[PDB]
Image (cartoon, coloured by chain):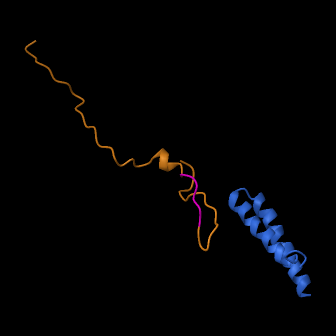
Amino acid sequence: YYGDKNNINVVTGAGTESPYNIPGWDLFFKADGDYKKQISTNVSFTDNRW
Amino acid sequence: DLQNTGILQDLENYNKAWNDFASNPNENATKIALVKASQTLTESVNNTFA
C-alpha cells in the first residue's frame, strides 16, 4: 500500500474537519477482526493394514 | 462598501482558495493560485494601509 492513513479531509467548522475516504491499507491489509484461525494438519491419515 | 469593500473580499477569495488547496492538497497548482490570493490580498492591505 502506498498512501497515508489520515483521511482526505476538508474543514468547514468552528474547529471541524470532514473525512471522506478510507486509506488503502484499511482495505489492503486491514484487520477484519471478526475472523478466526483455520489450522490443519498437512499430513493425512488412513488405515494401513492395506 | 465596494460590495464587502474589496479587501474584505480578498480574504474570501483567499478563503475559498484553501478549499481548493484543501481539495487538491498534493496537487500544488491549488497552492499557487491560493498563493496569489495571499499575495494580492497582502498588497491591497499594504495599498489600503498606504
**Image position of B35 (left or right of A48):** right
Q: Quadrant of residue B39?
A: bottom right
Depth order, front residue of B40/B13:
B13
Which residue sits at x=76%, y=60%?
B30
Q: How many marks?
A: 0
**Residue pushed farthest left?**
A49
Q: Is residue B25 visible?
A: no
Which residue sits at x=34%, y=47%?
A34
**Residue pushed farthest top?**
A50
Chain B representation colour = blue
Main secondary structure found in the magenta portion: loop
Q: Is residue B16 visible?
A: yes
The percent coordinates of residue B48 (x first, y second) are: 90, 84
Write the start and end of the magenta stretch as one range: A17-22
Please check the rendered image and state whether residue A20 is part of the magenta-colored stretch, yes or no: yes
Depth order, front residue of A42/B37:
B37
Which residue sits at x=91%, y=76%?
B2
Q: Quadrant of residue B1?
A: bottom right
Please check the rendered image and state whether residue B27 is part of the magenta-colored stretch, yes or no: no
Q: Quadrant of residue B36?
A: bottom right
**Image position of A7 (left or right of B17):** left
Q: Which chain is orange?
A: A
**Residue pushed farthest bottom?**
B50
Query: Measured along the vertical axis of the image, is residue B19 above or below residue B5?
Result: above
Which residue sits at x=58%, y=55%?
A20
Query: Measured along the vertical axis of the image, is residue B2 above or below residue A6?
Result: below
State which quarter of the image contains the C terminus of chain B: bottom right
